[PDB]
Amino acid sequence: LWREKINLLNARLAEAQTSEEQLQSQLDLQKKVVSDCMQRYLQV
Amino acid sequence: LDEAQTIESELDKQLRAANKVTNVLDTELTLARAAERKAQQTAQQGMKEEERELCASHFPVVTLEQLPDIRDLERQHERGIQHEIERVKAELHRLNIELT
Amino acid sequence: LWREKINLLNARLAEAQTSEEQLQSQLDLQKKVVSDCMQRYLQVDSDASVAKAKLDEAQTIESELDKQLRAANKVTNVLDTELTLARAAERKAQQTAQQGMKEEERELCASHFPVVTLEQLPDIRDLERQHERGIQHEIERVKAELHRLNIELT
């Protein structure tokens, strides 16, 4: 049963880490959006 | 620009929360593997099919839900077994007096 | 033992939260510095280029501080979970400890049962089982002696 719990927790932890990576990427993209806004302000 | 800076913070906080979730799942997985090896060190001993059949006829099958409570069932069976041991031993002592 | 552990974990969690909040304040101040350099890039090897370089440095430091705050958040969450587990165990210990004793009983227990240490605190149940096994051996030998005496007396 511990091996079965390991099987389940493997998928759960993998999905949690994937969500963490996605959130990190989206945070980087939001900082990139800040960069885009600053560039547009620089142009004007 | 200010709007984007404001939006950044919520994603940062959600990334921290995802870190927490990942760490909790990793801790549970690591402890599950530790308990797995702990039980396997005993599971290595095995049984002969007659012994396993007797155990099944006397012991319930542990379920994943029952995994945290396994010791309760094991101790309950042990204590019932000890009760039976003392009872039959007392009856044997009674018959010993009879034979004497 | 669990109450000592809970007080120590309260102190530890407070310190970890203080460190995480200090890093949060530093990260917010670094984002403010990023904003300052970003705005000076516009309100001003030219002055604009120097402000742009300052902004790059500020953003790098902001990323560094965010990555440090992540570790601090990890520490805070781990310590909070440990405190929760300590409280959960302490409530059970209190429930079982609340049954009380009389000083004769306490003398008997101490003379044969130890004062468990904090480091052994989670493992206390198995030590209790070992002492139970000792008492069980004494019982299961004395009873046999009674059996023998009964036989002879008959």
Image (cartoon, coloured by chain):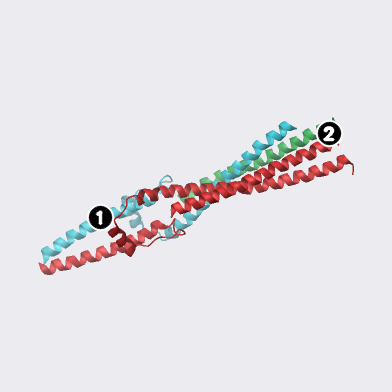
Chain colours: A green, B cyan, C red
Q: Position of residue C59 (x, y in %)?
A: 75, 43
Residue C125 is tagged as none
Q: Is residue A31 visible?
A: yes
Quarter of the C terminus of chain B within the rendering: bottom left
Check the residue under mark 1 and report the chain it is in: B
Amino acid type, residue under disc 2 in the picture: Leu
User: In front: C122, or C90?
Assistant: C90
Q: Quadrant of residue B99?
A: bottom left
- Crowding near pointer 1: few (<14 within 10 Å), some, many (20+)? few
Residue C36 as seen in the image, left or right of residue C149: right
Picture quarter with the N terminus of chain B: top right
Circle 2: element type: helix
Q: Quadrant of residue C129?
A: bottom left
Task: Give the SS element for disc 1.
Answer: helix
Q: Which mark is residue B83?
A: 1
Would you place residue C37 above or below residue C99 in this image? above
Q: Is residue C65 left or right of residue C90?
A: right
Badge 2 sits on which subunit?
A
Asked if residue B26 shows in the view, the reply is no
Amino acid type assigned to the residue bearing label 1 in the image: His
C35 with respect to B91 (left or right): right
Q: Can you tell which mark lies on residue A42?
A: 2
